[PDB]
Amino acid sequence: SHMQKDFWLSEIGDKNISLGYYDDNVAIVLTNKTDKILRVYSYEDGKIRKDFEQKEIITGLMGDKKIEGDLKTPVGFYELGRKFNPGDPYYGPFAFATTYPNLLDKVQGKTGGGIWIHGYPLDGSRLDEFKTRGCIALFNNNLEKFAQVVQDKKVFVMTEEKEKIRAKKDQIASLLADLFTWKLAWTNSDTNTYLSFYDEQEFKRFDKMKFEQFASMKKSIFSRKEDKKIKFSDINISPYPNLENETMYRISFYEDYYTKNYQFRGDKILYVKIDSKGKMKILAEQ
């Protein structure tokens, strides 16, 4: 059933999956770089609630971030770390670090870091789009409320450039069916089906291997024809804003496997697009 889109459509039902479909409760920090609005939404079993909002925020520069020093705020889907104290009053009372660069950023060769949500200089110095070095600044008098809303939660960061990016039920359902079809192909050492879920042109890796060599490597590995038992859990699927006019999603999950002497849980992440035929194509894989 898990390989059928309509099974997932039934599971999703009337849930609000516009900011993603999550196995458990999460918060989503949604920033739009054109609107200069940051909102925090809680997701509870498909019910969305707006818990925080500030308008007239300061972000970094427009455009897709590429390198250390370009001053741009990254567009995409990230995670937020716990409140911390920079120890420099320039950042306001405290800060929260986003995970820029993520795996997709890295395999695309992007550089930089230090993309945080923080406040304003305690001495009153003004901020502008050039001074945050890509960080997102909220007024200090709103940061206590922001901190309370994100405290002790699993918190994601969704940053749009201009267009409003929302997940669609049909896309989440089709991707979940593709995910479990890809899982079955790996389980059965079915090289051809497995490889059909990778973008022959755009899939990128740390080791810079091209698709032809990746295909032959996987066929070699799969030739062991090992009997495998694998379970996915804690699946989170999220829409992925981008400036390439692609329908992209992030899929994260735990990979579980029992061994006669150990049960292993490992974190998996796929960054994917939906191709013109409606099929998942993996662009980066942990």
Image (tube, grey):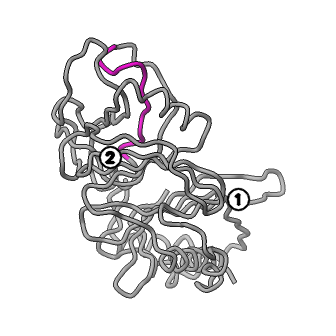
Q: Please give the name of the residue rendered at 56% of the width and 50% of the height, measured from the top-left corner.
A: 42
Q: Is residue 92 magenta?
A: yes
Instruction: Judge by depth and name the residue closer to the eye, 45 or 258.
Output: 45
Q: Looking at the picture, does residue 122 appear above or below residue 21?
A: above
Q: Is residue 199 magenta?
A: no
- Nearest the viewer among 213 and 201 is 201
**Which residue carries the number 1 mark?**
256
Q: Is residue 169 left or right of residue 163?
A: right
Q: Is residue 22 left or right of residue 109?
A: right
Up the image or down, 45 lies above or below 142; here it is below
Horizontal and vertical percent for residue 50?
Answer: 50, 50
Which stretch appears magenta? 89-101
SS for tag 2? strand
Q: Residues within 10 Å of mark 1 (few under 14, many from 20)?
A: some
Q: Nearer the viewer, mark 1 or mark 2?
A: 2
Q: Which mark is residue 37?
A: 2
